[PDB]
Image 1 (spheres, each protein chain N blue to C red):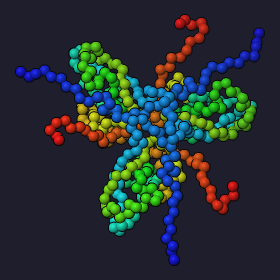
Image 2 (image 1 turned 90 degrees about the vertical axis):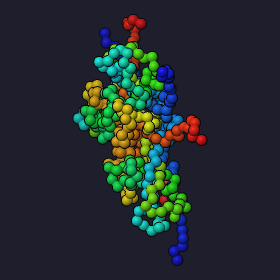
Image 3 (image 1 turned 135 degrees about the vertical axis):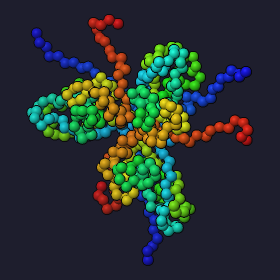
Image 4 (image 1 turned 180 degrees about the vertical axis):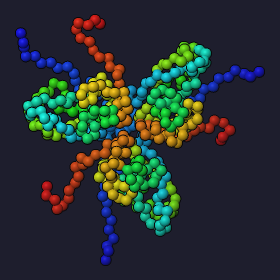
Length: 147
Length: 148
Length: 148
């Protein structure tokens, strides 16, 4: 008897808190690389397990350790509320993804490895090292019950 | 016989010669780290030994070598003439202080290790590798007793 | 049937496609280096072998491998269409040159090593360590005799 329900909370802004806007080149911050969108050996209807905030190395494989951390995936195809991207790609297909590399302020709490685990402290060094600011200073919000 | 005197030389903008104004995140250039303000072992009211321009690592320990250089202490509590913070703290307590990290131009001549010695030619790479321009072309100033 | 003919091809802004300008400094992207202009063997009246887009190390030696790339030489003395410095510097002299290091979007098709060889894929890593973008998405151009 379970009711069919859908949910949506959070936006792209919550991932990219801040950004340096280079006057001479608006694209100075982003590197575009190709990754496997639909998982391999899966049905055309198998929704991809790629989500905003997954760390990916410059090669394109999602990062499972501090070693492979190069950037943050912010592609417009994997933002919250993007649902109808089903079957438009074949298994094992490689399609371009956009990544943010340098000159950004990132939300510490939402960066996650390929498995979804939060970024290790040793991994934060890679992001901090190159361009970016990683900060967990977030206000949060209260909805109901919590006066 | 030792007439009490005080001196002021330099200020905040005399170290951070230039800054890249990040849009949206105005704190893109700075980090906050907890540091031991009053020495762990010292008199209850001994002034802290920290001075502006001292190199500091990621954990807040003053950098004694190029290996531990991460940033430059910039916080307002250590600027010249801010001695009114004496006695407030207690030995062994750690207090946050702002550090400068990236996107800045730094006056080399005022960067010194914890011991007060001048920055090393190897440690300069760490600061420059962070996205900063360490420079030496400073006009300087000359006072009475110099022919101009 | 021989006539004295001269030609000009390019510009300065096709190497540094974009640049981030800092409020504090308009010159924190670059670095000035001491470079040898005329080799120690070629007589005084001979053209220099450098060109805009040659990768150089910090010590001023033109880059020969991906492990030594530090910046791109974009000084205004070697821009295309100048050609008036022949014989002004005797062999072995050392002259300052303006390198471009940080905060740039750099063309790849014009970057080259010491001998003119194109930039290796593993040499892009060194140049992006300074925080720059190496982009190949250049429309190019096509002159008379071509369709479109």
